[PDB]
Image (spheres, rainbow, N blue to C red):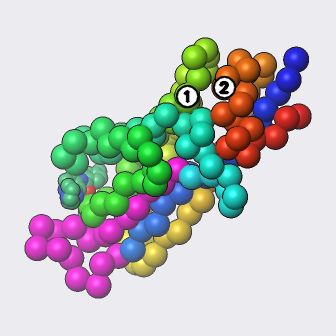
Amino acid sequence: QCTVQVRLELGHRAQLRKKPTTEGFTHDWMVFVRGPEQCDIQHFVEKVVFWLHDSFPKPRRVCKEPPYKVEESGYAGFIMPIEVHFKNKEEPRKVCFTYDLFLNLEGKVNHLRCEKLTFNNPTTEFRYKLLRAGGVMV
Ligand SMILES: Cc1ccc(C(=O)Nc2ccc3nc(CN4CCCCC4)[nH]c3c2)cc1I
């Protein structure tokens, strides 16, 4: 009976371009998954999959190593599913967030969403990956 908590930070920045691109993109944005300061989520994260709006080319964007992010331009916000896959042999194998990639049509957005994962009775192997990433026993 051991519990290990880890923290993920999901976020995005978005800025209204001074002048739109020749292709009518009004906004640059960047979305990411990371750990807090001094933690290393690559120890227990296999890959992060960002599911972009179906209008984007290759909207299944995968990062297998850090940084777990996508940098894009576009013209609108949307709801972006983000799957974080674990280096876990048992359940849960992954967690899915629905991320609100919203834009400020009149300027800049800099948003952070903090997600605390609780793993009950991880395998010895996966427990090792969580604590090495900076996870805490509860
Ligand atoms: C409700 C909605 C929200 C966002 C988009 C959008 O911005 N789509 C989009 C579609 C294609 C794109 N292509 C780029 C520019 N490239 C993409 C490939 C890598 C280099 C940058 N940005 C793109 C943005 C479309 C809709 I309707």
Please give the label number shown on residue 126. Answer: 2
The residue at which mark 1 appears reads as 87
* Quadrant in the picture for residue 41: top right
Q: Is residue 3 left or right of residue 66?
A: right
Q: Quadrant of the C terminus?
A: top right
Please give the label number shown on residue 54. Answer: none
Span highlighted in magenta in the image: 16-33
Q: Residue furthest bottom?
A: 18
* Quadrant in the picture for residue 52: top left
Q: Is residue 76 above or below residue 89?
A: below
Q: Is residue 116 left or right of residue 16?
A: right
Q: Are marks 1 and 2 in contact (CB under 8 Å)?
A: yes
What's the amino acid at mark 2?
Answer: Phe
* Quadrant in the picture for residue 60: top left
125 or 18, which lies in front? 125
Q: Residue at x 22, y 48 (%)?
A: 56
Residue 61 place in picture, x, y as percent:
32, 43
Residue 48 is one of the magenta-drawn residues: no
Residue 55 shows in the view: no
Residue 19 is one of the magenta-drawn residues: yes
Q: Residue at x 70, y 41 (%)?
A: 132
Q: Residue at x 17, y 74 (%)?
A: 21
Across the whole image, how many numbered discs are drawn on residues? 2
What's the amino acid at mark 1?
Answer: Lys
Residue 123 place in picture, x, y as percent:
71, 18
- SS type, badge 1: loop
Q: Is residue 65 above or below residue 122?
A: below
